[PDB]
Amino acid sequence: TYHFQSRRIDVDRDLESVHRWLGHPKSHYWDMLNSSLADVEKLIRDAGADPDPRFGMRIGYFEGERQFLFELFNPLTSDLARPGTGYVYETGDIGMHLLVSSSERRLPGFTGAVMLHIMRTAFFEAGARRVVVEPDVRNADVQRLNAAVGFRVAGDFPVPGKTARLSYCTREDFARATDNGRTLA
């Protein structure tokens, strides 16, 4: 079964893969279809530009091959911090986005193992006390991934072109839901 590691993104080597993944139609919620390599470099650079080194994009690996990208972002420089969204920032909050590779063929439980790895990384390596996500309400696959690791829906809020579904996963809710990262809810 899947056991993942991850490392910080390397723009000098990862651009080709990340650009490919973003061009797959299943990645359309990232809004980077038909982007150039330079467009993807800017996406990665912007994600890496917070002063705090805990934030930025990471690449997951299994058996020597890239498997996914995840971004641990600063909520206070994201859409979440727009006045009036209803997000209530707590010290230690970290945002997360996930991009899976464009490979189609997986072993059982791929995205559950992905999510367990991301959440453990956020809490134990990046010091998060709570993970916050704001996917498009129409992105039903993400809602299932969220539930699998203990996220609770807080509500929906409008951003231009999108209704976002705000969900939170405290370290406490993750540990209870997954038996300390052993399994899915």
Image: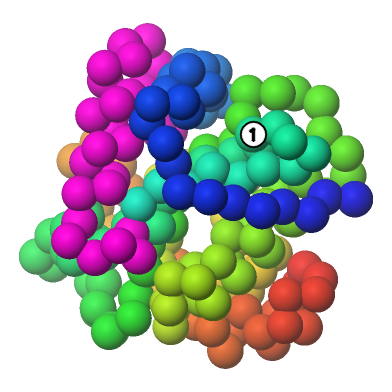
**Rendered image quadrant of residue 10:** top left
Please name the residue shown 35% across and 65% down the image.
54
Q: Residue furthest front?
A: 12
Range of the magenta residues?
29-55
Classify residue 44 as left or right of residue 178. left
Residue 182: x and y in percent read 80, 75
Residue 47: x and y in percent read 28, 45
User: Which residue lies under the disc numbered 1?
Assistant: 66
Residue 41: x and y in percent read 29, 26
173 w.r.t. 72: above or below: below
Q: Quadrant of the C terminus?
A: bottom right
Magenta segment: does it hold 75?
no
Please name the residue shown 64% across and 34% down the image.
66
1 w.r.t. 75: above or below: above
Between 126 and 23, the one lying in front of the other is: 126
Magenta segment: does it hold 30?
yes
124 w.r.t. 36: above or below: below
Three-letter amino acid code of the residue under disc 1: Arg
Please name the residue shown 17% across and 61% down the image.
51
Q: Residue furthest left?
A: 83
Please name the residue shown 40% across and 17% down the image.
33
